């Protein structure tokens, strides 16, 4: 019955759609699509929507900036709706995990450096692995690439599973997510 704010990181520009570094947007779009939440409110270029997962009320947000998502979008909304920090889930692409690999973590480089810059370890977080830039590709290009066919199959799987994970977390907490999703227990 305590609400969650679920935010996915990315960029609303058209060129970013379906690219590696935008996968958190895809995830929140799936969540909202699957949970019946309409995201038709804009704050600048950020998109939001309110609905619920089961009886739990949830606000889903796609902040327009990678750099300042907290301050811009998440913080003010969470405040208004009085969402505890522990119920602000961030979802984003993680170059530190292989493509498609999901990881749900409670609160507490490059990935690591970035995380440490933005304070993301203070929230529960769903990482969607995208792997790291090969050989020595321009990181800019790498992040902008669209998944290859083989990679997309893995990412589809992750998006499918991700919805369920998030639904679980919201409905049964970390403990329920553990129970349901961890092989090793």
Image: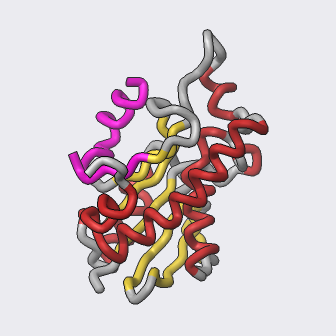
Q: Quadrant of residue 75?
A: bottom left
Which residue is at the front of the view, 136 or 62?
136
Q: Residue at x 57, y 58 (%)?
A: 27
| Residue 30, percent from left and from top | 61, 65
Q: Is 36 one of the magenta-colored residues? A: no
Q: Is residue 84 left or right of residue 36?
A: left
| Residue 46, percent from left and from top | 56, 62
Q: Quadrant of residue 131?
A: top right
> Magenta residues, as a range?
103-122
Q: Residue at x 49, y 47 (%)?
A: 92
Q: Relative to 52, say whether 33 is above or below.
A: above
| Residue 2, percent from left and from top | 27, 81
Q: Residue furthest top?
A: 136
Looking at the rendered image, the quarter that the N terminus falls into is bottom left
Which residue is at the front of the view, 33 or 165?
165
Q: Residue furthest bottom?
A: 55
Q: Residue at x 38, y 33 (%)?
A: 114
Which residue is at the front of the view, 181 or 73?
181
Which residue is at the front of the view, 179 or 123?
179
Q: Relative to 25, say whether 114 is above or below.
A: above
Q: Is residue 97 left or right of residue 159?
A: left
Q: Is 118 one of the magenta-colored residues? A: yes
């Amino acid at each position: 019955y305590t609400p969650w704010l679920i935010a996915g990181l990315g960029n609303p520009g058209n060129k970013y759609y379906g690219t590696r570094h935008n996968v958190g947007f895809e995830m929140v779009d799936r969540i909202a699509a699957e949970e019946g939440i309409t995201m038709n409110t804009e704050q600048s270029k950020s998109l939001l929507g309110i609905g619920s997962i089961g009886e739990v009320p949830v606000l889903v947000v796609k902040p327009q900036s990678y750099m300042n998502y907290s301050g811009e979008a998440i913080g003010p909304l969470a405040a208004y709706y009085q969402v505890p920090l522990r119920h602000i889930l961030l979802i984003y692409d993680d170059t530190s995990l292989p493509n498609g690999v999901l990881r749900l973590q409670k609160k507490g480089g490059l990935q690591n450096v970035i995380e440490h810059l933005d304070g993301r370890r203070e929230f529960p977080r769903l990482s969607i692995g995208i792997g790291s830039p090969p050989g020595k590709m321009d990181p800019r290009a790498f992040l902008l690439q669209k998944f290859s066919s083989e990679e997309r199959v893995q990412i589809d799987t992750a998006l499918e599973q991700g919805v369920d994970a998030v639904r679980t977390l919201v409905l049964k907490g970390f403990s329920g997510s553990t129970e349901r999703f961890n092989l090793v227990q």
